[PDB]
Amino acid sequence: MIVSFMVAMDENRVIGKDNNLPWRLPSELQYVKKTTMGHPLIMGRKNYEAIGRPLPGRRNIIVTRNEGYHVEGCEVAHSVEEVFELCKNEEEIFIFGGAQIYDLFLPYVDKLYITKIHHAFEGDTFFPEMDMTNWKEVFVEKGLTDEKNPYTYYYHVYEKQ
Ligand SMILES: NC(=O)C1=CN([C@@H]2O[C@H](COP(=O)(O)OP(=O)(O)OC[C@H]3O[C@@H](n4cnc5c(N)ncnc54)[C@H](OP(=O)(O)O)[C@@H]3O)[C@@H](O)[C@H]2O)C=CC1
Ligand SMILES: CN(Cc1cnc2nc(N)nc(N)c2n1)c1ccc(C(=O)N[C@@H](CCC(=O)O)C(=O)O)cc1
Image (cartoon, rainbow, N blue to C red; front, side):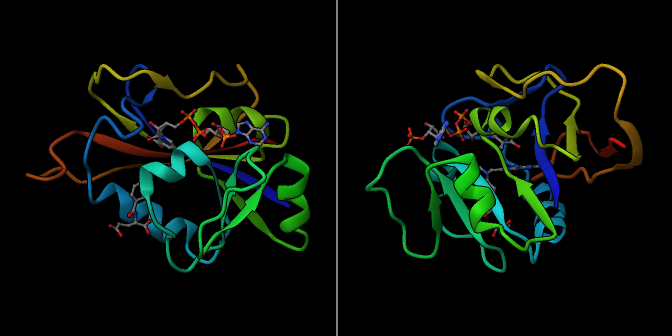
C-alpha cells in the first residue's frame, strides 16, 4: 500500500511543545480532516492523548507497547508489523505522527503531507529530518489567515518514486 506521513510543522521543524500543538489553528484541522477522511490513522499513544477522542470516519489505530491499553472506538497495535497486519488490504495509510511514530515508519514512507507554519514557536518535539534529494514535490498551496488562524501557513505534498 501507500504509506503517507501527515504532519504540521514550524519554520524550524517544531511539531509540539507540551504534549500538545504549540498553536491553535482550527482551519488547519480541516484540510487534515478532508485529506484523511475514509482512511486509517496511525498515531502514537502520546499523540492520541493529545487528541483525547476517536476522530470520526477513519480507523484510529494507536501505537503503544502497553499490553493493557484500550480505548473504545480505537484499535491498538503494539508493533509496526501489527499495524501492517491490521491494515491488511488497505490502499493508503496515514501516519498521523508523534515523532517516535514518524521514526518507526520512515523505511516504509511513500509520500508526505506537510503544512509549514512561517513562525517560530519554542516547542520541543520535532519532525525528523528526511531524504536529501529523492522526494519530488507535487503540490503547493497557501492556507487561510484570520483571527483564529493568525499565522501564515502553506500546504505541501511530496512523493518519492
Ligand atoms: N504538529 C503535528 O502535525 C503533530 C504534533 N504532534 C505532537 O508531538 C507530540 C507527540 O509526539 P511524541 O512525543 O514523539 O510521541 P508519539 O505521538 O510518537 O507517541 C509515542 C508513543 O508511541 C509508542 N511507541 C513508540 N515506539 C513504539 C514501538 N516501537 N512499539 C510500540 N509502541 C511504540 C509509545 O507508547 P507507550 O509509551 O504507551 O508504550 C510512545 O510513548 C505531542 O506534543 C503532539 O501534540 C504529534 C503529531 C502531529
Ligand atoms: C493534536 N492534534 C494532532 C494534529 C494536529 N494537526 C495536524 N496537522 C497536520 N498537518 N498533520 C497532523 N498529523 C496533525 N496532527 C489534533 C487535535 C485535534 C484534532 C481534531 O479534533 N481534528 C478534527 C477536526 C476539527 C474538530 O473536530 O474539532 C478531525 O477529526 O480531524 C486533530 C488533531
